[PDB]
Amino acid sequence: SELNIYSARHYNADFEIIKKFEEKTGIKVNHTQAKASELIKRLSLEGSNSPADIFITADISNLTEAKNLGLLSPVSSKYLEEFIPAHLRDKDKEWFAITKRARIIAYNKNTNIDISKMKNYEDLAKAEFKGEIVMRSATAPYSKTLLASIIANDGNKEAKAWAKGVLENLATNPKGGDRDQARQVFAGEAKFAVMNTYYIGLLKNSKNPKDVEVGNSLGIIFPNQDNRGTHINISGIAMTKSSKNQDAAKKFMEFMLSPEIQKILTDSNYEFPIRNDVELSQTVKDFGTFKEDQIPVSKIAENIKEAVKIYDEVGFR
Ligand SMILES: [Fe+3]
């Protein structure tokens, strides 16, 4: 009858998906969108009394934070286990990926720009790029999880040095999110933006012609192709321990991995599907092929607390 979703996703495509669920099942969805940090705090304070049934994020670490705050409940679904690879879901069955996305370095391909020395995440922190980089706030999930991945791969001293150098190199204080950083590259205010791949698709296919202009100017560097490969993060989903509509919650989680919905996620939101039998949308194919970091996303997320402290220490936020 009702299903209460707390979502840190921030996409128009989700509205269509939810309508399709309502149409299919007759269940009314109450959709609450806010920042992940706000939702996790809210879930903690509301506790067992929360009306929430579902927590959706655009980030692995937010799911693990929620798990480790005792806020989620395990789901044993043959459907989810068949179609989500084990490396993309919790061993303890409390969180499950619905998409993949890659955090890349974007440049203005309508300029002559030498990208030969901007090859790895490490390079963003190099003195030669002072004043040439833009990135959103350190408090953003994408930023926290990227730094956590650097800790996991290269250690906490490289992480701190990276964070410090990135801060020093920013063309501007962080101003809005990925699409705003992309506009700064379009406008020539910075040479390189740290951003997720799907935003390039959203922009290029936008019904707002100004978004199309921005998206059309972007080239992609997939970082670290000569070594470990590019940072992958997930959007994902969990049932809350507070859930009183558990059947609906499980139905919704399975619906997010259904063929039609995985196709919408790539066709309409330009993300990578989790299912291995869903063709990429043509825009996403145009991003190109690339090497992905093989690290389990769960292992990245083990470093989230320290990532927060490092960004705080070097002077973000
Ligand atoms: Fe996003």
Image: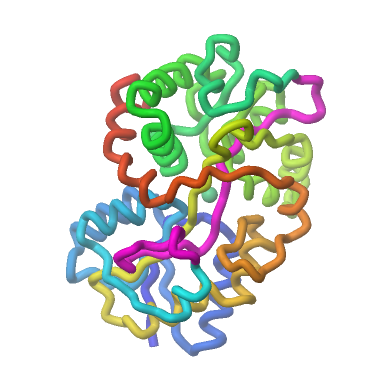
Farthest residue in the top direction? 127
246 up-or-down from 42: above or below: below
Left or right: residue 83 versus residue 72 is: right
226 up-or-down from 268: above or below: above
The residue that appears at 70% across and 29% down in the rendered structure is 107
Residue 272 point in image, percent of width and height:
61, 57
Closer-to-camera residue (83/306):
83
Closer-to-camera residue (286/195):
286
**Which of the 4 image quadrants contains residue 315?**
top left
Please state, as top left, top right, bottom left or bottom right, where the N terminus lies in the image. bottom left
**Which of the 4 image quadrants contains residue 111?**
top right
Residue 296 point in image, percent of width and height:
43, 50
**Which of the 4 image quadrants contains residue 114?**
top right
The residue that appears at 39% across and 22% down in the rendered structure is 158
Residue 154 point in image, percent of width and height:
41, 29
The residue that appears at 73% across and 49% down in the rendered structure is 208
Q: Give the residues drawn in magenta, as a range.
A: 85-113
Left or right: residue 219 versus residue 262 is: right
Confirm whether residue 6 shows in the render.
Answer: no
Left or right: residue 214 versus residue 104 is: right
**Residue 111, magenta (yes or no):** yes
Left or right: residue 23 versus residue 86 is: right
Label tally? 0
Closer-to-camera residue (24/227):
227
Closer-to-camera residue (75/217):
75
